Amino acid sequence: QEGQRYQALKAHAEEKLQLANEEIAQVRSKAQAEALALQASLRKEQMRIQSLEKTVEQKTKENEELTRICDDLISKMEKI
Amino acid sequence: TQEGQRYQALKAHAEEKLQLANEEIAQVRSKAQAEALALQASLRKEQMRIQSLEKTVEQKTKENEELTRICDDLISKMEK
C-alpha cells in the first residue's frame, strides 16, 4: 500500500523530530547558562576596575597629604 | 491518487515542522555565539585596563613609600 510506505517512514520522521526538540531544549539551556556566566564575570571585572580607580584616587590623595604634612613640618622648622 | 495527496500533505506537515525546529536551533546557536564573543571582547578589554590600573597603583604606592620614608628620617633626626 501507500499506507505502508507512509508509516514505515512515519516512525523515523517522528524520531528525527523528537531528537530535534531535545536539542532545541539543550541549546536554549546552554545559551542562557553562557549568558549568565559571561555577564557575571564581566560586571565583576568592571567592579575591580572601579575599585582600582578609587585605590588610585586615594594613593594620589595620600601623596598630596604626605607632601602637605612634611612641607608644613619643614616650613615650621625654618621659622625657629 | 488522492490518498497520495493526503500522504503528501501529511508528510509536508511533518517535514515543515522539522524544518522549523532546526531553524530554531540554528537561530539560537547563532545569537548565542554572537553575543558570547561580544561579551568576551568586553572581558578582554576590562582585564587589560585592570592590568594597567594595577601598574599605576604599584607606582604610586612606591612613591608614597619613599616620601613617607624620608619624612620619617627628617622627623627621627629632629627627635634626638
Image (cartoon, coloured by chain):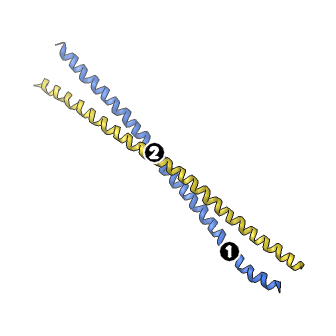
Chain colours: A blue, B yellow
* Closer to us: A63 or B26: B26
Q: CA distance from mark 2 to mark 1?
A: 44 Å
Q: Which mark is residue B46?
A: 2
Label 1 sits on residue = A16
Residue sitting at the far top:
A79
- Tell me the SS state at disc 1: helix
Residue sitting at the far front:
B1
Which residue: 72% across, 64% down? B20
Q: Quadrant of residue A21?
A: bottom right
Residue A2 x %, y %: 82, 84
- Tell me the SS state at disc 2: helix
Around disc 2, counting alpha carbons within 10 Å, would you say few (fewer than 14), some (14 to 19), or many (20 or more)? many
Which residue: 43% across, 47% down? B47
Residue A47, relative to residue A69: is it above or below? below
Residue sitting at the far left:
B80
Position of the C terminus of chain B, as image quadrant, is top left
Residue B21 x %, y %: 69, 66
Which residue: 85% across, 78% down? B4
Image check: A61 left or right of A33?
Answer: left
* Closer to us: B24 or A39: B24
Image check: A23 left or right of A8?
Answer: left
Chain under disc 1:
A
Residue B73 x %, y %: 16, 29
Chain under disc 2:
B
Position of the N terminus of chain B, as image quadrant, is bottom right
Residue B18 x %, y %: 71, 69
Q: Quadrant of residue A66?
A: top left
Q: Which mark is residue A80?
A: none
Q: Amino acid at mark 2?
A: Glu
Q: Amino acid at mark 1?
A: Lys
Around disc 1, counting alpha carbons within 10 Å, would you say few (fewer than 14), some (14 to 19), or many (20 or more)? few
Residue A26, relative to residue B53: is it above or below? below
